[PDB]
Image: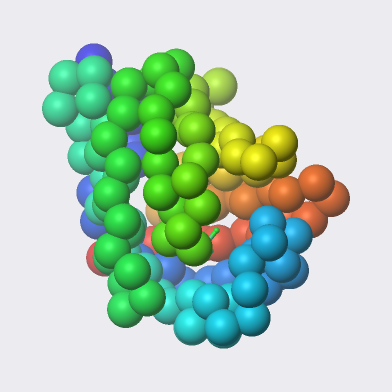
Length: 134
Ligand SMILES: CCn1c(S)nnc1CNc1ccccc1Cl
């Protein structure tokens, strides 16, 4: 109970850095990178008991995951990878690992001031995406 309270709400993307290079490193193709890089998603996070739901709504795609911390699940990502995901809380940071085709990427979500900061890492490449309350 109360684990992710500071994450809950409706959030709007306000800045992005290095996302094209992150997407390249993940293997996303040209057209998807261009269209996806234009999107300004809203991220809606909610908690009901032990189940966390993260929805992303954008002009590119609407996605939704629900999960229990530490419990692996199947995810189809916005760029159409079929991945196996596990999300844990590490020192107040939501840590989301995706595995597919022998590859791995980690997405960290943390509260910093009034922002929700999303750090996406693939090998040596990091993208930082900043959300504010909608
Ligand atoms: C990385 C998390 N994320 C944030 S933050 N905004 N959208 C996403 C979903 N990922 C994604 C979206 C489009 C193309 C490629 C990818 Cl990997």
